[PDB]
Image: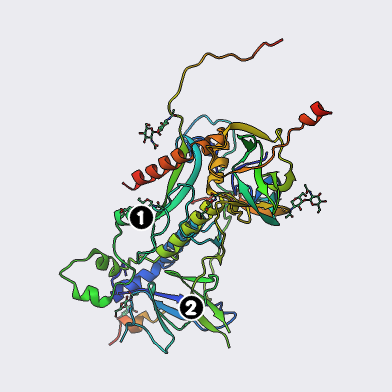
Amino acid sequence: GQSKRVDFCGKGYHLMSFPQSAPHGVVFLHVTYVPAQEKNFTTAPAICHD
Amino acid sequence: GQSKRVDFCGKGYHLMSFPQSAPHGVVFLHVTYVPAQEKNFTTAPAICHDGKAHFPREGVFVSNGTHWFVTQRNFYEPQIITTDNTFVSGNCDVVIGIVNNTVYDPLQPELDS
Amino acid sequence: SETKCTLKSFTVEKGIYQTSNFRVQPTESIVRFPNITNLCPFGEVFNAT
Amino acid sequence: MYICGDSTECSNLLLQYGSFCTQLNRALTGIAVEQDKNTQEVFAQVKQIYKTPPIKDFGGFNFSQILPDPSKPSKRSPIEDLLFNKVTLADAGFIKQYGDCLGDIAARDLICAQKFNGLTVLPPLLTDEMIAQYTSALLAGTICSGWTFGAGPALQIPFPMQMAYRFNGIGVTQNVLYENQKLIANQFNSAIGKIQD
Amino acid sequence: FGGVSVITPGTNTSNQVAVLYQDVNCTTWRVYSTGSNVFQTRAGCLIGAEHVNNSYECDIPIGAGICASYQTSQSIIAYTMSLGAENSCAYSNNSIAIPTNFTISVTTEILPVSMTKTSVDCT
Ligand SMILES: *[C@@H]1O[C@H](CO)[C@@H](O[C@@H]2O[C@H](CO)[C@@H](O)[C@H](O)[C@H]2NC(C)=O)[C@H](O)[C@H]1NC(C)=O
Ligand SMILES: *[C@@H]1O[C@H](CO)[C@@H](O[C@@H]2O[C@H](CO)[C@@H](O)[C@H](O)[C@H]2NC(C)=O)[C@H](O)[C@H]1NC(C)=O
Ligand SMILES: *[C@@H]1O[C@H](CO)[C@@H](O[C@@H]2O[C@H](CO)[C@@H](O)[C@H](O)[C@H]2NC(C)=O)[C@H](O)[C@H]1NC(C)=O
Ligand SMILES: *[C@@H]1O[C@H](CO)[C@@H](O)[C@H](O)[C@H]1NC(C)=O
Ligand SMILES: *[C@@H]1O[C@H](CO)[C@@H](O)[C@H](O)[C@H]1NC(C)=O
Ligand SMILES: *[C@@H]1O[C@H](CO)[C@@H](O)[C@H](O)[C@H]1NC(C)=O
């Protein structure tokens, strides 16, 4: 599945995971989306048209 | 509530549950939705109309033997691909696997009539 | 008082405490031996020629 | 074995409280049962075994370090082979023969010392090969049909559309994925390589 | 030196048992008896069970992939357990499967909530 629980399936936004076998346990490879370059913009809650 | 946790409230997509009493414990009856009959369709990531690239808003582009339709992801109910079922982003030279089809425009016939 | 002794306190807070068990005492004793009237042969065992 | 060591006089005295030994073993048996149960709950979730696909172009997405390596005696993925080589177990296999412990006395092997005092290690029900097969089925399922194999029947989907759905699922419109497909696939492939290292 | 366990069908069915010798290789074996039906596995030398080449679902687990059951003229057999049904899909870059119908399923989950409450008078 695709969990929405924060930091449950790794840091960042979860996309998918792949298990791997290990002696006496399991290892998960968690693939996540992480925001990178960003810019600062002016903002507003609403637009006044007519 | 209605949990979205996979296989938490039973296998399949959870709709609702009903508890029942039991000695020393609880028994849950979990009602889930399960996909049944299915069909194989040809697909594409985008539609190329007038050179612009059209993507589904809430669905997938699906083709039968001769025509392209857009359907909701979990249920086969074909709709005509129109400008109200898609959004436009970029153009036909970027998306890998861009089929060309007509994206019906519901306004033009009114402007013509 | 049994609760107070168990808790080692002269003060008991609100709640339910288990307090030992209901017990009764014996009132009399019974002795039942076979009705043997002969004395053992102490003479024969210890006074033998 | 642990307490008396085959001394007959001790054994006969031990019987004075033999209900104790029975109780100790009920407790250990219960633990052993749970260990096999725990393994199945984590790995044997899907009883439908999907085979690892021929490697096809998945849209630039390279899964070779997570999928089984068919050239090896044990079809472990490159990552799994590394994980297994790094964790060290007490011994190899569950058969230790009397004649091996009798011959190698000078060796002072701790495993024989434990066995002669009544301490035994039992084998797992699922072997490493069996665990690898469950893992492979889950990976084959995910790559071929995404999450649908969990929900019910598996429904095939192009890998890149599976990714589009996953992007919409985090609040990023799918046109981003298709427009940047080469970049996304390259970053993915790079990240997996870094993990094995 | 140890290593012995017994595989039993219920005694209300039969009195045949198989005995596993955990530390015996069998390939004068430090066993109580033979009588053929000797199968060697990673979990030990199993004496008193017929090896079967068919996989089945697990009934009495033995260990290391081997399970046993009582089956037909019934006797104890041993086999490698099945891990599940073979299934398949056909990954393709241009096709999708889409559900056309659905079913409503109701399943049952059972959980303990509480245990017996006790009190003990040590005297
Ligand atoms: C794909 O779907 C279309 C739309 O339902 C099918 O075309 C229609 O077929 C009916 C007869 O069953 C005609 O009366 C309609 O006029 C057709 N519509 C159009 C636009 O031509 C089409 O046959 C289906 N293709 C295949 C291969 O089954
Ligand atoms: C997936 O990535 C691996 C590398 O992790 C690729 O394997 C390498 O291929 C080059 C060129 O043939 C060889 O020189 C290397 O020795 C290979 N490395 C390893 C570890 O095998 C593999 O070809 C890529 N798969 C696909 C489908 O592109
Ligand atoms: C967004 O980030 C990626 C890196 O994750 C940038 O891609 C790299 O760009 C440099 C400069 O052209 C190349 O030398 C690298 O080879 C690229 N990396 C990969 C994996 O392709 C990308 O240019 C950034 N882009 C924006 C804001 O458009
Ligand atoms: C032994 O004999 C004497 C008399 O000579 C007597 O006084 C004594 O009580 C006798 N002992 C026992 C045990 O009867
Ligand atoms: C039993 O001994 C043989 C050598 O005769 C060996 O090949 C085999 O692996 C051993 N069996 C087990 C379960 O280790
Ligand atoms: C699928 O792969 C084949 C090559 O095996 C290629 O010819 C075809 O154009 C590809 N289709 C899509 C939608 O990527």
Instruction: Please name the residue that numbered disc 1 is placed on.
Output: D78
Q: Residues within 10 Å of mark 1 (few under 14, many from 20)?
A: some
Give the quarter of the image for residue D13.
bottom left
Give the quarter of the image for residue B89.
top right
Specify the amino acid type for callout 2: Ala
Q: Nearer the viewer, residue E39 or C43?
A: E39
Res. A31 in view: yes
Q: Is residue E27 above or below residue D107?
A: below
Residue D32 at x, y = what percent?
44, 62
- How many marks on residues? 2
Instruction: Please name the residue that numbered disc 2 is placed on.
Output: E78
Q: Residue at x 39, y 45 (%)?
A: D192
Q: Nearer the viewer, residue B94 or D3?
A: B94
Res. D34 in view: no
> How far, Cα to Cα, is label 2 from label 1?
33 Å
Q: Is residue B89 above or below residue B67?
A: above
Q: Residue A45 vs residue B110: left or right?
A: left
Closer to the camera: disc 2 or disc 1? 1
Q: Quadrant of the C terminus of chain B?
A: top right
Whether callout 2 and callout 1 share a subunit is answered no
Q: Is residue D196 above or below residue B92?
A: below
Determine whether the residue tagged by mark 1 lies in a helix, strand or loop: helix
